[PDB]
């Protein structure tokens, strides 16, 4: 995350860190709790490392230093990458992770509501990725305005969402992929976007791109059975 | 394709024809669309004409005759031949083409999925080669795209079959013991694909041999899954 302030604990209980830890761990990507045994994240996070048993998932934390031997992790029972996703492009950048053991929610770990079709205000982003360019131990926060896609074009499908100041200076960078773009409306927080890609980490006029969760609901419901 | 049959329109929408204008414009290789601006092919296709500006790339067609000099072709912005490939030699025989201009996906022009490193134990039972190559050992390029189905022949038995050359892990062998069904001259760089699940996957790229359907001498194919890191690296 870049352009943004440090994270209160409990403020974003749905945020998880996906880590691989082959022999030792490493935070590679973010994700969102959406169900007791379900995390939503970006397909491209698993390009280099599609091996599910190697991944480890941590929620309800703020400082990655808190993770230790006696820190319960979640495991991937099943990794469901969209079938149209292809490594060479940013289309269909979405993935469901079915957890091995269903979580028991707390003050610090709870799900996000999926979007059920409007004009969002108060949209936010989070993550453990650097500002500018290394990895931060403490989760981060920045507020951002949606950019209409048709303007976003400066190929961007109906399945994408864009956000960013075109003055620039706040966006997400590596390690923030698969993390959530959320919005606060009808009094309720919703998960509107999944961070996917943008050229650079936004500088000046480069809005970031996000998978648009609402247009993948059929998919998500289909795959959760 | 020796021992094949006509493809239908839209059947193999990732298949492209790689041509060059020497005399009349001429088909020299095949290739596979793997993204809007990415085409995967064989590196030995450029052995004699390693000048990118010269090549025209055509997709979404069944008959090469459909191609008039008024049909729009894609051009090569960037030719990425694998770092370790050497010209006469048969290893690392793979190349990425970055197109000058994004393609438009249609019914007849689609990309094909690549295999995942987590697919590498998969046993594929339903495999196909397609191309405009010769249909007999000494023959002519074919107007209508050919298809042929052909079984994978495991590494060790394929090595047995080729005493003089070395068949490494980066390759993959397909053919019948009797022979008679194979890729021929003009099919190089084209796709070997396999249906697994409900999904087509690019499993190989036609490479060497071009014995063109000799007895017990399976066509040899570049094993795509072996190059995922390379591809991921080059396509960013
Ligand atoms: O009829 C199907 C078509 O298939 C191809 C060739 O066999 C043509 O002669 C034929 O018209
Ligand atoms: O005919 C060329 C066409 O190619 C495809 C799309 O990019 C269209 O916008 C364009 O008109
Ligand atoms: C969050 O808090 C850390 C403490 O490590 C500071 O580096 C900085 O104030 C950031 O906003
Ligand atoms: C509730 O679920 C938690 C998930 O971690 C387990 O520790 C346990 O099975 C309990 O029933």
Image (spheres, coloured by chain):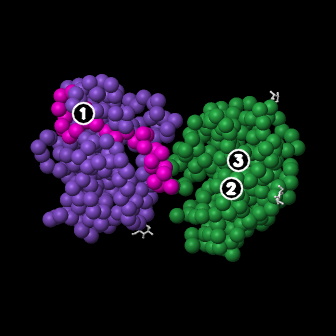
Chain colours: A green, B purple
- Spatial CA distance of label 3 from label 1 is 49 Å
- Classify 10 Å Cα crowding around label 3: few (below 14), some (14-19), many (20 and above): many
Q: Quadrant of residue A6?
A: bottom right
Label ID, residue B165: 1
Image point (22%, 28%), residue name: B163
- Spatial CA distance of label 2 from label 1 is 48 Å
Disc 2 C-beta below 8 A from ligand 3: no
Residues shaded magenta: B209-236
Residue A143 to residue A70: above or below: below
Query: In this image, B114 relative to A130: left or right?
Result: left
Ligand 4 located in image quadrant: top right
Q: Nearer the viewer, residue B7 or B104?
A: B104
Label ID, residue A134: 2
Image point (75%, 40%), residue name: A58
- SS of the residue under disc 1: loop
Do marks 3 and 2 both belong to one polypeptide chain?
yes
Do marks 3 and 1 both belong to one polypeptide chain?
no
Q: Quadrant of residue B105?
A: bottom left
Looking at the image, do the residues carrying marks 3 and 1 touch, with CB atoms under 8 Å apart? no
- Spatial CA distance of label 3 from label 2 is 19 Å
Tell which subunit mark 2 falls on: A
Task: State the image coordinates of residue A156 (x, y, percent, origin top left).
Answer: 56, 63
Tell which subunit mark 3 falls on: A
- Name the residue that disc number 3 marks: A31
Query: In this image, A148 relative to B184: left or right?
Result: right
Q: Residue furthest right?
A: A107
Residue B9 to residue A170: above or below: above
Residue A48 to residue A119: above or below: above
Is residue A114 in view? yes
Residue A143 to residue B192: above or below: below
- SS of the residue under disc 2: loop
Image point (31%, 59%), residue name: B58
């Amino acid at each position: 995350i870049v352009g943004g302030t440090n994270a209160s604990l409990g403020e974003w209980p749905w945020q998880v860190s996906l880590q691989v830890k082959l022999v030792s761990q490493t935070h590679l990507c973010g994700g969102s709790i959406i169900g007791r045994q379900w995390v939503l994240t970006a397909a491209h996070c698993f390009d280099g490392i599609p091996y599910p048993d190697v991944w480890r998932i941590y929620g309800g934390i703020l400082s990655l230093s808190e993770i230790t031997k006696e820190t319960p992790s979640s495991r991937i029972k099943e990794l469901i990458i969209h079938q149209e996703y292809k490594v060479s492009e940013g289309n269909y950048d979405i993935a469901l992770i079915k957890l091995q053991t269903p979580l028991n929610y707390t003050e610090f770990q709870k799900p996000i509501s999926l979007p059920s079709n409007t004009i969002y205000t108060n949209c936010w982003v989070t993550g453990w990725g650097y500002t500018k360019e290394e990895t931060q131990n403490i989760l981060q926060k920045a507020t951002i305005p949606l950019v209409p896609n048709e303007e976003c074009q400066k190929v961007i499908n109906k399945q994408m969402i864009c956000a960013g100041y075109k003055e620039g200076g706040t966006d997400a960078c590596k390690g923030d992929s698969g993390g959530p773009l959320v919005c606060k409306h009808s009094g309720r927080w919703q998960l509107v976007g999944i961070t996917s890609w943008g050229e650079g980490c936004a500088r000046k006029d480069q809005p970031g791109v996000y998978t648009k969760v609402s247009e993948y609901m059929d998919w998500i419901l289909e795959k959760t059975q």
